[PDB]
Image (cartoon, coloured by chain):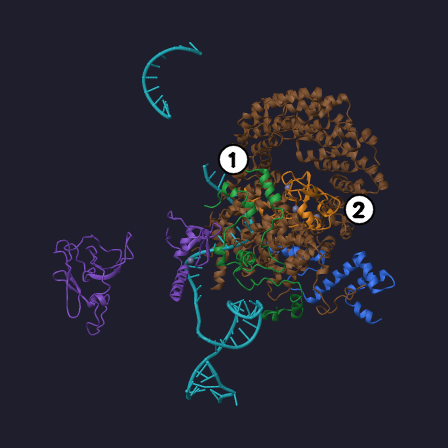
Amino acid sequence: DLMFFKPSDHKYFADVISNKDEKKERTLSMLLLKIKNGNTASRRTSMRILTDKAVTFGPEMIFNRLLPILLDRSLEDQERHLMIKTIDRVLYQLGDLTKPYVHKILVVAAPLLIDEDPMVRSTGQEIITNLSTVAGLKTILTVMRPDIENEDEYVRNVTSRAAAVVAKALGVNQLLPFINAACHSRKSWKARHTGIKIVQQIGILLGIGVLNHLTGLMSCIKDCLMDDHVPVRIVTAHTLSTLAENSYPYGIEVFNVVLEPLWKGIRSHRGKVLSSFLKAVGSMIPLMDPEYAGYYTTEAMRIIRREFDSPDDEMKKTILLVLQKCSAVESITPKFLREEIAPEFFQKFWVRRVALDRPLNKVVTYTTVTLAKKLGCSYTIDKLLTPLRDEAEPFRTMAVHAVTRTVNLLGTADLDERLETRLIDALLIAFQEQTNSDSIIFKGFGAVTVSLDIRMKPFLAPIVSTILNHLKHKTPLVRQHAADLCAILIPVIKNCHEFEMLNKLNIILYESLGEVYPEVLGSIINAMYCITSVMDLDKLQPPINQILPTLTPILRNKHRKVEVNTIKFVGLIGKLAPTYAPPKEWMRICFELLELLKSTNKEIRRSANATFGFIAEAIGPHDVLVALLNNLKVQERQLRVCTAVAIGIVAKVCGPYNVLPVIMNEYTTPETNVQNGVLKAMSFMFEYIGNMSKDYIYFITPLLEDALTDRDLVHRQTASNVITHLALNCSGTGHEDAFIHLMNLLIPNIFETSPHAIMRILEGLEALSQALGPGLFMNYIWAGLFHPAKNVRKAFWRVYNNMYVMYQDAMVPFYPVTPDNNEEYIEELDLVL
Amino acid sequence: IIEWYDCDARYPGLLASIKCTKNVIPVPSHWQSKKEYLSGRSLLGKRPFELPDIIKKTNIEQMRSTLPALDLDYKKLHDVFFKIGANWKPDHLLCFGDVYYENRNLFEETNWKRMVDHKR
Amino acid sequence: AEKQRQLKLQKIYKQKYIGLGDESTTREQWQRNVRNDTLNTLQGHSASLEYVSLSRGDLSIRDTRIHLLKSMSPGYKAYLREE
Amino acid sequence: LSKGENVPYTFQDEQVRSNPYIYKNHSGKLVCKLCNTMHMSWSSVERHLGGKKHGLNVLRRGISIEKSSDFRQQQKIIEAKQSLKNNGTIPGSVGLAIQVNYSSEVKENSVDSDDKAKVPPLIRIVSGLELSDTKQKGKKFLVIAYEPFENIAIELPPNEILFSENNDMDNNNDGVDELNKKCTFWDAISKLYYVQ
Amino acid sequence: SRHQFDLIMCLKQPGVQTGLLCEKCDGKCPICDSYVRPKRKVRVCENCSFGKQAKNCIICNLNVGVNDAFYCWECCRLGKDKDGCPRILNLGSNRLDRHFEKK
RNA sequence: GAAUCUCUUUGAAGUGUAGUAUCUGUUCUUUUCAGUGUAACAACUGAAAUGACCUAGGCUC
Ligand SMILES: [Zn+2]
Ligand SMILES: [Zn+2]
Ligand SMILES: [Zn+2]
Ligand SMILES: [Zn+2]
C-alpha cells in the first residue's frame, strides 16, 4: 500500500519509480520503503520477508542503501526506529561484517545513546551490543582510535558511550588496554578527556560488576588525575564519584591510592574543581574505614560549612550530596549535627528560591531525609513546620515531600503534642490553600495520618470538615484530589470508632456519585470502596442494596479509572454482601461485565474476570456459565480468552463438579473458536485448583482425545496447555496410566513447528516428565535421541535439553548404557553385594 | 527394528544399541513425511465428540443443545464424578508403547476390544 | 527471534549445566556426560557410595569416592594401567 | 456469499446438495473431501472451486468412477404442434409412422439469421424414469423437438417395434444417431416431419 | 518472557535481595506470568540491583515497583524458580513500538 | 395547587507487537556428468559432442 508517501526520502530512494542483482536490488529497497513509509500490515510482512531473506541479500547493498537513510534530518522517531529494528535484526542475522561497514553502522546508530529518552537509549545500546559480537575486539578498537582524536565534543561524547557499551558487551578485560591507550595517551588532550569518560559510562553500565575490573581503571584515575588540565582533573573527580557509588564500600583498599591527591586538590584549587573533588570524596565517605571515615569526614565538614554560601548551583548540589553520604557516618554524632550542621543547614538551604527549581529540589529533599535519620525526627520536622505555612505553593510542595519521605522512614512518634498539633494544622492549611495541581499532598498527608492515627481524633473531625468543603468545589482537580485523600483517610477513621461519621461520608459521596466528570467519579467510587471495606455492611447507611443498582449503569461510562474503581467496588460487594443485591440484578452485572471486558485495560479486564468468582459464589454458577458460554462464540480474542478466565475462576470458587460437564458440552459444539475457549477455560480452571483435578482427570482424557488428535494446531496447542497445568498439579497422584495415554498422543506433535506450538508442546512434555517420571518419557526420548534425520534429532534434543535441565540424577539410572553400548561404560554399576 | 536409513546414522553401532534396547519406544514414523503429520482423509470423518456415559447421565445433554437456566443439583453432579464415577475410567486409554499414527482411529479398536468381550 | 533466543538460552543452560546435547553431539562428548553424571550420583549419595564401597571391597569408603572422582577424567584408565 | 444454502456437517450422516463435496468437519472450518483442503471462508471455498486444483481432483474422481464401473439461447414458445399417428405395416412386421406438421410461414418470418435454421427436427427415445413430477413411470417416449415449437412425446409400451436389422448398406454419416438417419424424413419445403 | 519473545533474561545465581514489581504488574509469576497460588519471593543477583535500577519492575523493567514478585507453584515445581535471576534487560519490541507509536 | 375543553400515542466504528494456518494465482525437465546439499530425495552450483555402425543395449571405434 505504501501508506504515507515520503516525497523527499522516496525520491532519495529512486530505484524503481514504476538481472538477479537488479531484482534483489529493487525488491530490497522496496521492502525498506515498506518498513519506513508504508502500511502496518504491509511493514509487518516486509519485516518477515526481509529477515528471512536477510541472509540472501548482500550486506553491501543492504547497508549501502539502508544506512544513509538515517543521515537525513527529515526522519521521525517512529520511522528512524522502524529502520533501527531492521538494523538490529539484520546485524544479528548475518553475524559477520567488514570493518568499513562496521564503522558506518557504529557511526549511524552511535548517537542513539545520547537521546533524551531511555526508549531510544535502549535500542541504541542493542545495536551496539549486537554489533560487538559481529565485528569483534580488534575491529572496534581500530574504529574508536581515529574517532577519539576528533575535535568534536558531540561525537567524542557519542563514542564515549558507544565505546562503553562495547566494553560491557565484549568485556572490559579485552578492551581495557585500549582504555589504557586513550587513558594514558600523552598525545591528545581530548583523548585523555574522553578516555576518562569512557570509564564513567563503563562504571555506570556495569554497576556492581565494576568491582573485579576496578584495578585497571583506578590506574587511569591515579595517573591521569595528576594532569595539569583542569577539565581532565574534574572528569577524574566525577569518575571517582561514579565508581565509588557503583563501587559500594568494598573498593576502599584500591581507592586509597587516589584518596590522597583529592584533599590537596580541595584545599588549593577550590572553585568548581572543589565541587567535583568534594563530589568524589563525598562518594568515598561511605566506603571509608570507621577510623578513616572519622578523620576525613571531620576534615570535610569544615569545608562544607564554609561553602554553604556558594552562589553556584553545581556546588550546592554537590554539598547536599556530601552531607547526604556523610550522614551515614557513625563518627559524627547526632548531637554534633543538631548543634552545628543542622541549624546552619535549615536556615541556608530552605530559602524560597531553593524551591523554584525541581532538579535541585530533589537533592534538597533526599538530602534532608538522609539527615532525618541521624537528627531527631521531632527536631527535623520542628525545623520543617515553618516552611509548611509559607505562601509559596511550590515551596509548600517541597515542604510536603520532606514530611512524606521523612515520616515514612521514621514516623511521627518522636514529636511532642504541641508541634504535632502545629504539624496537622500546617498540613490542613497548605492542603486547603493549594493553588497548583499535583498528586503529592493527599498521598503524603495520608502517609502522616497512617503514621499517627489514634492521636488524630480531635484533628480527625476538622480534617473531614475540610474534606467535605473540597468535595463541594468547582474544580475537578481539587475534587478528585480531595476524594483520593478521602479513600486514604477512611481506614484511619476506623481507629477512632467514628463509624457514624463514615456513614455520613458514605452518604455525601454516594449522593455525589452522579457527577459528570469521570476522573473525579472514579476516585469517589474508590472512597466508596474504602468505606464499605472498612465499615460493617449492616450499619452502612445508603444501604448497599440501594448502592449497587446505581453502580450498574456506571460500567458503561467508558474511560478507564471509572471501571477500575467501579469493578473493584462491585467485587467488594460481591464477596462481602451476597444477600443484599437481588440475583437478577447480579445477572445484569454479569451481562454488563460480559460486554465490558472488551476494554483494552489488563487491570479492568483481570479484576473484571475476578469478580465472576464472587458473583458465582453468591448466585447460580450455571446461571453465570450460560452467559459465559454464549459469549464464547464471539470472534474477539480478548472476549474468548477472558471469558475462559471467568469460567476458570467460577470453576475455582464453585468447584469443577458443576462447571466441567457443561464445559464438555460447549466443546461438543462444532465451532472452532468455542472449542478453543473451552480448552483454555479448562487450562485455567485446572491451574486454579491444585488438589481438585486429581479426581477429575479421567473425565478429561476422552475430551483431550479429540483435542490432541484434532487437525488444528490451535486445538493441539491449547490442549497441550491443558496437559501442562493438569499434569503439574496432578503429578504423583497415581494417574500416570492416564498420563501415559495423554503423552502417547503428544509424542507425534513434537515435530510440529511454529514458536507457540513448539513451546506449548515442550512445556507439556516437561509437565509429563513430572507425572510419568523420566523413565518412560526417557524411553521415548532415547529411541529418538540421535537418529539420522538432522531434523528429528534437532527436535528431540530440545526435549532432552529441558529434561537434562530439570532432572539429572533422576535420569542417571535410566541411561540405556551397556558395556557393549559404550567402551568405558562404568565398572562400578555391575557390583552386587 | 533397524531400517535402511540407519545406515547414515552418524554413530550407527550406538544407535542400533539404543534403538534396540529393551524398553525404548521407536520414534513415531510420521517423520520423513512433509504432510505436517495430519493431512488425514480420516480426519475429515472423525466424530466431533461423545460424552462419557457417566457424564451423559447428568442430563445436561438435554438441558443445553450443543448440536445445530440448565440448573442441576449439586449433589447430583458431585455424586456423578465421585459417588458414581470414582471407579470409572476411560475404556480405551493406551499402553506403554502405544503411539498414535495419523491414519489410526482408536474408536473402532474400542468397539473391537469391547466386542471381543461381549461376543463369544 | 524466538529460535534466536533459544540459541542464547542454549549457550546459558549449556554453560551452567555443562553437557546438553544441542543438535550434533559426538558420542565421545555425550557418553562422557553420561559417565560423569552416573559417577556423580554414585559418589554424591552417601547411600550409593556406602553401597559401592562394600560391593567393591575397598579398605576405606573415601577410596571409592575419590576413585569415582578420578574415574571422571578419561586419562584415569591409563593412570591405573601405569600403576 | 453462501446464497442461503445449508452445508451439513461431515458427521451428520447424510435434500440434495449443490456440490456434494464442500463440507464442514467436526470443527467449524470448511473442507473439500476430495481435495482434502481446508478453507477459512466461503470466499476461499469459491476460490477453491474456481481453481484448477479442485477440478483436477474432480477429473481424477471421475476416472475413479469409470474404474469402479447453444443451450442458453434456445428459443422456446412452447407451442404444441399437430401430430398424426397412424398404424403402419410392411414386409415382415408392424411399424409406427408419425406425421408432424409445422407453421405456415406465420411466425417464422421474424427469425431468419441462419442460426441452426438448417437444423431439422430431432427425435430421441426417453425413459419415463425421469420426470418433472416423478410419480409413475416404466415406459418409453419417442420425443420430437424443434427449436421454437414445444417438445412432443409418444408412449411406446411395446418393447420393440420396427427395430430393423441393417436396412441400408452401412453408410456412415451419423448425423445425430442411427435412429435419425435410419428412419426419419424432413420435408423442409413443406415443413412436414415424418418418422418411422 | 513466556509471551513476548524478544525479552531477554538475566539467569545468574540469585542473591539475598528480592526483586520488586510495580502495582501494574502485580500478581504475575515473572516466568509464566500466572496469577495463581504464588509461592516463593523472587531473588535477583546483586548485579541487577545496585542503584536506581533496583527499584524497577523486574517484569516490565520501566516502572518503579513496590511489591515483591513471587514464583507460582507450577514454576516452583518446574524448578524455574531456581533457574537464575529473572529480569528483563531489553525493553522489547512491544514496549518500543508502543512508545514510538504514541510519540 | 385545583377545575374544564381539544388533539396525539398505547392497550456507532476503529489499534500495535511477534507468530500461525488456509485458498487462489504463478513456475517445471533436451540429455548427461562432478561438487554442495539431503535421511535419500529434492534443491542449488559448474561444463558440455561430433561422427559412424548393429538387434534399451556397446570390455565399440
Ligand atoms: Zn476440492
Ligand atoms: Zn540478574
Ligand atoms: Zn511492572
Ligand atoms: Zn510461574
Which chain is represented by green in the image?
A: B
Q: Earlier in the sequence, mark 2 or mark 1?
A: 2
Q: Which chain is cyan?
A: F
Q: Quadrant of the C terminus of chain A?
A: bottom right
Q: Which residue is mark 1?
A: A591
A165 over C33 or under it: above or below: above
Which sits in the foreground, E101 or A63? Answer: E101
Q: Which residue is the site of mark 2?
A: A250
Of marks 2 and 1, the one in the foreground:
1
Which shade of the palette goes to chain A?
Answer: brown
Picture quadrant where residue B2 is located: bottom right
Q: Please give the letter of the chain rendered in purple.
A: D
Nearest the camera: A26 or A579?
A579
Q: Residue A584's x, y, as percent?
A: 53, 31
Q: Is residue A375 left or right of residue A732?
A: right
Mark yes or no: residue A810 visible: yes
Q: Which chain is orange?
A: E
Q: Nearer the viewer, residue A421 or A249?
A: A421
Chain containing the residue with disc 1: A
